[PDB]
Length: 48
Length: 48
Image (cartoon, rainbow over all chains, first blue to last red; front, side, top):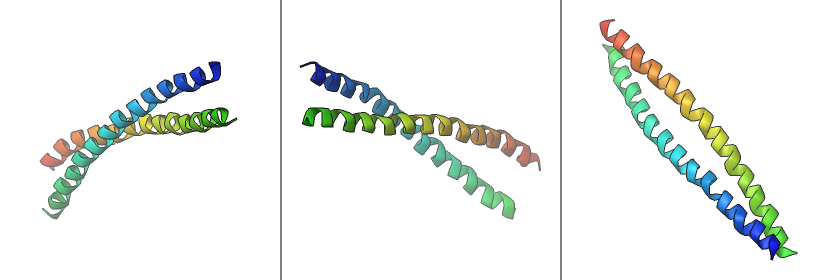
């Protein structure tokens, strides 16, 4: 009865880790998408 | 026996997310530095 509440409580503690990871991974797909626009804005600027 | 086998499995699953957060928390800055430097260097390049 007490060991399950360790397991019930830790699955709450797994959540905010996974909660923060999607908030992390949403940013790294966001900034990189702009970052490859900085590359596409440079490949023409180099040719100029 | 099995519920304690369920605990250390998902506690080991907690170690990946705690690592990957600490992986992501370093990466979100170290792209942003090479983002915000690029956002400054490009305006310098426009005069070039």
